Amino acid sequence: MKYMITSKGDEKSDLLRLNMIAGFGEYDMEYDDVEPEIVISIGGDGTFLSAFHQYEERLDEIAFIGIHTGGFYADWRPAEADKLVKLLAKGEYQKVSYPLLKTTVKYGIGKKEATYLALNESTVKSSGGPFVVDVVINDIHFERFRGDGLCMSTPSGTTAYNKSLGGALMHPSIEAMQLTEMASINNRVYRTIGSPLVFPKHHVVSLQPVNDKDFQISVDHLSILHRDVQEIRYEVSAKKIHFARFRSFPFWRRVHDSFIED
Amino acid sequence: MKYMITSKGDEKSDLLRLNMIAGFGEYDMEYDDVEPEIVISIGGDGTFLSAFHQYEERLDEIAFIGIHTLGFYADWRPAEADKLVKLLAKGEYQKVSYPLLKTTVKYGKEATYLALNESTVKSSGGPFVVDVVINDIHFERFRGDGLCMSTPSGTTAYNKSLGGALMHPSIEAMQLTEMASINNRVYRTIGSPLVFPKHHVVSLQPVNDKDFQISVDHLSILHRDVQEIRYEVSAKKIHFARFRSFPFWRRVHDSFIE
Amino acid sequence: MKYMITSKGDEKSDLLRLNMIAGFGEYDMEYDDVEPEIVISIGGDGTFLSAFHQYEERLDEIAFIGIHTLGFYADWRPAEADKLVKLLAKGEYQKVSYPLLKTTVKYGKEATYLALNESTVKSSGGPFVVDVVINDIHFERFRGDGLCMSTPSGTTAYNKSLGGALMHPSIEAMQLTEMASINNRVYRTIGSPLVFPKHHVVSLQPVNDKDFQISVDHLSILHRDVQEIRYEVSAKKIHFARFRSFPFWRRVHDSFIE
Amino acid sequence: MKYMITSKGDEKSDLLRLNMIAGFGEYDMEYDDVEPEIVISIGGDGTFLSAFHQYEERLDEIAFIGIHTGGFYADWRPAEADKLVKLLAKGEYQKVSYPLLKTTVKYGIGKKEATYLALNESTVKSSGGPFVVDVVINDIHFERFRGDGLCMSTPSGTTAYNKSLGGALMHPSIEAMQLTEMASINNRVYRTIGSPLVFPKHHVVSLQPVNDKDFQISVDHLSILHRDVQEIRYEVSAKKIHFARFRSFPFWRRVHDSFIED
Ligand SMILES: Nc1ncnc2c1ncn2[C@@H]1O[C@H](CN2CC#Cc3nc4c(N)ncnc4n3[C@@H]3O[C@H](CNS(=O)(=O)CCNC(=O)C2)[C@@H](O)[C@H]3O)[C@@H](O)[C@H]1O
Ligand SMILES: Nc1ncnc2c1ncn2[C@@H]1O[C@H](CN2CC#Cc3nc4c(N)ncnc4n3[C@@H]3O[C@H](CNS(=O)(=O)CCNC(=O)C2)[C@@H](O)[C@H]3O)[C@@H](O)[C@H]1O
Ligand SMILES: Nc1ncnc2c1ncn2[C@@H]1O[C@H](CN2CC#Cc3nc4c(N)ncnc4n3[C@@H]3O[C@H](CNS(=O)(=O)CCNC(=O)C2)[C@@H](O)[C@H]3O)[C@@H](O)[C@H]1O
Ligand SMILES: Nc1ncnc2c1ncn2[C@@H]1O[C@H](CN2CC#Cc3nc4c(N)ncnc4n3[C@@H]3O[C@H](CNS(=O)(=O)CCNC(=O)C2)[C@@H](O)[C@H]3O)[C@@H](O)[C@H]1O
């Protein structure tokens, strides 16, 4: 099929790329940078996200693969690159899909709505001052949050930032999204739930400003400033990321290898 | 149809049950506490958990209703009992299902327990050390006070006090949470809570002591010669008779926020 | 003696200050905002923190009073302002001291900052990595959102939201708390908060970026070319004029419990 | 001076003991099991606590030393035992003192008061049912606690159980005690502070029962059942444990070596 490869930038990753492109040529396989079907990422999880977001408009026609150079989303060590070209050329793989998080930001008098898709998470922090938003879950005013910010994570994203916030680890087969607090203030005048929340596939969380309307919104490795925000909407995306897998690397085992030693 | 009513025991709960039985007596509603299709609980969640475990062998045939006299599982206030009698006589309700936890203990038979809130494992009295196997993976050797495995609807209970997350009951999953784990240069646990899907099995296997203080909801018993505890989302569900809209996130708000 | 009054700025706070100045005008009380021995703050803790930093070069000569119009540092309600005028004119007060945090930033001079609540260190925008040296010990290489070093009286503020502990102000110590640290198979931080005594020095030294967003109480400024941040219990203290018994644990109760 | 040695029980620790006693004999030093002045512990931190509590009535006349066989309170590796006998016989050491926690339990119609001294901590848990106590700090009813129990730790005890509860690590030069919660219930009907508390040398925390009066009280490696408890009192002890130190092993470095790798 059509493929492309994104490099991290260092000398190692680049040469591995060329070498993989040289092997791919030997098998009558076409490099298509515009509309590929297999996207290969050589680098780290930062590099994998870069590739995911490079092709977020063709996620239904793409099956990602990662090669870890320096990798939660990687399944291949560099020394396995030649083997991966072969198995790939033979079509000896099975597609697997993880859930994604849709982020919608409504802002301005024009009520523009920017929609973002996130693989790890989307976070919301203020412009420097106090962060205060109302958390609306569907039709329920759940709480008025005051603190450093809010993190909304995918299942596969719970082992990243979410984890550092005290969130829980969810198996990627659970089409859910998780909301964790960042240094929430809690006394008698202000209260939050203080517990992470896990929302199912049909629920919508709507963050609404209370005073200042400027917010720093991150989507995975990105961080955008939005002014005059009226609403930040969170929901499990209908779109899913597809991985081309050739062997068994269960999620918990991947959790075990990343955080548990001996 | 056939029903029963279980009471917390106090004077108020007892009279309310008597009054409702007298109201059902005006309809084709048969009191039968051996084979009830409707079980009404009058009391707190402790009462409701008791009623659930009193009929765990026929959950597939029963619809539970809770009347609160904190009532997380109760949908009804005591003043509206008479209204509940009529609405139930008229069959003006839908059936909602909540997922449950299957807890299996095998020795050296095999005792199986269903849970609505959670199941925790602590030590008889000494050091608590157990290996945590997930499916075919030896995930970690836990060293602490104990472990908690809760249902979605139990995440707002003991799981919440442990730092776990609250999961909407539409998710068929179970969450595992540590109790004061040890993390030094050697001993290492994940720390984070864990949320497993319906097709996963969490197996706790002893390392040193084989006696464990095992809990299922409000019940706690010393189990001896334990060779394994296995947790997994039960194929069985608990069914409530729902009369008006009362979403889960709303109950969570009312119980903790304001 | 010489005094001054600083106001939050709103209409009520401004008039109250005017009314008190008119009351002090009946006693040998000289208004002097260059060299005041008594500084009165009318507003919130944000006002009080501002007043403190407006006179940090003469803390050894000033006694602070706080009038609340959440007021953790305020001892006085607005209705009792007139009573405060008389009691202060009569010298009917004792002096209580709270410990402070010394924050030193050295580049490639050396800026020094006193703190009443805390000092936090975050990243300009990229990854935050800093080595944490305690005295002559390389304790850990922190990887996270940032770090918070608070005074005893600041432990009820930002330090509390981070999970730190509340320390009674009679303890001359400072507490360090992490902000969303990273703990995987490689990166490893202590996790627990740290409480250091008066004779210890906590030095944060960059690894990669040398630009840090540094905060002292309510002030936050981008510091560039930072070579080190050093934290240590300041030899200096903040002095309040205390008129009635109001213990620290009582203020904590009123602010968080009921 | 007069010394004694407590062994863990295994074959290694016992032989090291005898061998140290053989060396101590060579230096005209007297083993006194009743009223020693140096107490040496060979084993782990569990063994060290056993020795501390074996001699809690002569803490003003004793200087403890630990040898780690399998040790937060140890300063010596077994291969250093001969060296320790020599330096000890030469009096080449400096005494250092850590704070301790006094625990007083008032119980029964007779209002008996049992007083315990703890090196790590003292914890309070119920008889199996619900645990509900009022926390009185001096003359202030601070909170009514509902949960699994309460932990009160010494400075040197903050790196043990306290740590596992989310408490903070205090340098042993701070004569304070720290209170951490065990799975406190928090909703709208019940509230706790949720934060660890650090009390100074002059403050007294008084746990008072609300309903049931039976409690399981632990003091370091011990756990006693007290019936009809009226009050559990906590305060920094006037007594301090003395260590004979011969070299620099700073507390934070000891924290570093125990929990921080590489
Ligand atoms: N305080 C925080 N704690 C934990 N995670 C955080 C924090 N702040 C941000 N993040 C995550 O960073 C992602 C952005 N990042 C790419 C990645 C990634 C990634 N994803 C996963 C995953 N799914 N599971 C498990 N580990 C994963 N990691 C690993 O994380 C490290 C990168 N983070 S950093 O080097 O500390 C600074 C931020 N780095 C970037 O700019 C690029 C690497 O070792 C990587 O391998 C965001 O999306 C947040 O999630
Ligand atoms: N440290 C703990 N923290 C939090 N929960 C704990 C703790 N220890 C045990 N549990 C739970 O108790 C259940 C058993 N319990 C009946 C119930 C219930 C119940 N279930 C839910 C739910 N699903 N969501 C939201 N609130 C819920 N609650 C409420 O919880 C309180 C009961 N806890 S108690 O009175 O403080 C002492 C223990 N109580 C019993 O003997 C009887 C009541 O207000 C009740 O209304 C076990 O199953 C554990 O889970
Ligand atoms: N995520 C955070 N959570 C908790 N505290 C935080 C957080 N971020 C910053 N801070 C502290 O704010 C101080 C600066 N702040 C003035 C004050 C104060 C103050 N000091 C104490 C004290 N010692 N004990 C007990 N309560 C105290 N409070 C109360 O705190 C609230 C202010 N926080 S805010 O309005 O939500 C947003 C930030 N506010 C400002 O701009 C001005 C008020 O009700 C106040 O009354 C810094 O110094 C950080 O410490
Ligand atoms: N959930 C818990 N998490 C953390 N600590 C706990 C927990 N439960 C009890 N404790 C402590 O145990 C002491 C009793 N214990 C002797 C010791 C000790 C000791 N003291 C210190 C110290 N000051 N700093 C740093 N590490 C220290 N350790 C180390 O701790 C382990 C022992 N705990 S155990 O093997 O998990 C089960 C309980 N063991 C006993 O019966 C005997 C060893 O590796 C030891 O080296 C109590 O006093 C609690 O503090």
Image: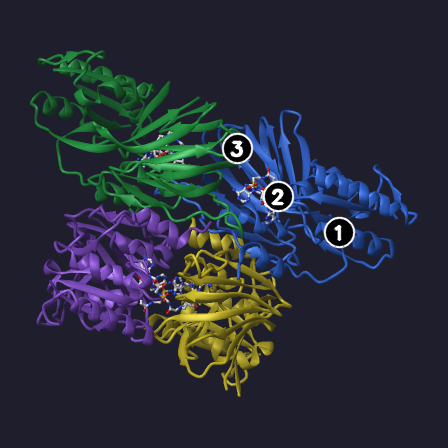
Chain colours: A blue, B yellow, C green, D purple
**Which secondary structure, mark 2?**
strand
Q: Residue at x 42, y 61 (%)?
A: B181
Report in which chain the residue with disc 1 lies.
Answer: A
* Pointer 2 residue Cβ closer than 8 Å to ligand 1: no
Q: Earlier in the sequence, mark 2 or mark 1?
A: 2
Q: Nearer the viewer, mark 2 or mark 1?
A: 1
Residue B198 versus residue C42 in the image, above or below: below
Residues marked 2 and 1, same chain: yes
State the residue in front, B60 or C46: C46
- Percent of width and height locating residue C17: 24, 18
Q: Which residue is mark 3?
A: C208
Q: CA distance from mark 3 to mark 2?
A: 34 Å
Q: Position of residue A39 (x, y in %)?
A: 78, 45
In space, the residues marked 3 and 1 are separated at their CA atoms by 35 Å
**x and y, in percent, of residue B124 in the image:** 37, 76
- Whether label 3 lies within 8 Å of ligand 1 gets the answer no
Residue holding disc 1: A242
As drawn, is C93 to the left or to the right of B222?
left
